[PDB]
Image (cartoon, rainbow over all chains, first blue to last red; front, side):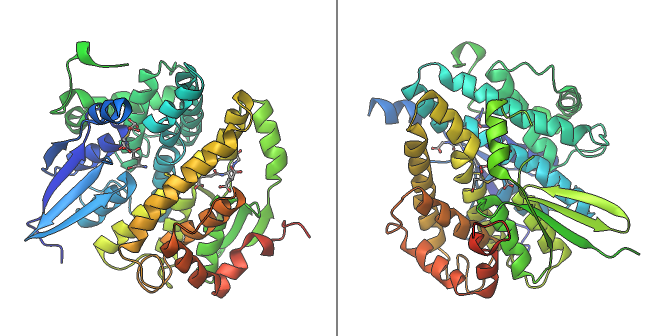
Length: 220
Length: 215
Ligand SMILES: N[C@@H](CCC(=O)N[C@@H](CS[C@H](CC(=O)O)C(=O)O)C(=O)NCC(=O)O)C(=O)O
Ligand SMILES: N[C@@H](CCC(=O)N[C@@H](CS[C@H](CC(=O)O)C(=O)O)C(=O)NCC(=O)O)C(=O)O
């Protein structure tokens, strides 16, 4: 049953792009949740000098707890459980398109720049991790720019936000982090600007999260 | 009215394409097989900064319009929505989320690490690193997947019928074997793989049955 007293708890790190996607689905659906910070920096530093993954959406209903993992799985659950406002359109072609744009990020871009990948690159070849990240992010953004520019609306798919924007916006933030020039992706930059003006996008941004450090205490 | 026709751009040994071959076979859907010369393609990509594209692509024509569906997971979701029976997702919200997470552990969490471009770039910087990396990341993904699958598996990854989860698992185990990984540490994955292998659709989708497989 779609029991209505579910409470939600998100395990999140302020600048995790994977967690940010889920923050965006939650914000866009107008869903309240408890923020449970997971300090991935502390865990990295502790593990170095010698498991907890993000996102996890914990759903509690009357003494039963469900732990939902994988951003895409979590977002598809949100869309089934709370269908309005829809972040997938009702037509099947559009659904496939939106899922493909999400997957270009989910599977095609982010994994190549995740923190474990980058750490293992730069252990073998100092400095190369950031060059690698820029290469693979640029490749993913080029695929997106082409696939989006196709009959583009104001957003990645039509004239309202969808799951595709939930994946695009955090990925462009990571692109900027690594110093990738975004000049070649004008459609993506336009979409990013349209999203940035919306209250739910503002709410989900890293800088607004409970665990966000001030600017002068952030690593690159 | 032009009724729906399916054409799959595939390469016999591509795990991403195989996933979609499994969805199509499980649903009893005929399709035209369109072979892609992936090895020639990847040689070009490597020499040209991979600017040029991926399989699978499912080309669908209906009512005079053509749709090119990309990304295995998006294609498989479309097949499940467009042709519901037999179902490759469970009916209940919690089981759907579990099956999608299992699928994504492979789709986003294991296969990208071992993508031919990723391994070529490693191999260009440090010869042999590609093998070490693939083995590390596939084993890591499979270890996590074993734990997750064991909590909910029946005969198959989720309960007692095949689901999208098994469409991701089976090709990924075949790739693990290509990289020489011991599969002993994943007994649940192996038992599920064996249950799937016995089924006609899995047999039909396997690399060795495809038109582009070597003699
Ligand atoms: N495909 C998964 C990706 C999850 C993921 O990469 N999570 C990272 C957070 S995203 C972040 C990079 C980012 O901002 O994209 C990273 O740490 O890699 C993580 O939890 N790392 C800690 C760990 O595994 O122990 C998903 O979509 O949920
Ligand atoms: N997340 C995507 C993955 C697609 C993918 O990696 N496709 C590979 C084929 S899968 C294969 C590796 C495999 O067997 O997994 C590989 O050759 O990299 C491909 O077409 N590469 C050529 C290119 O990018 O130009 C999807 O699920 O469709």
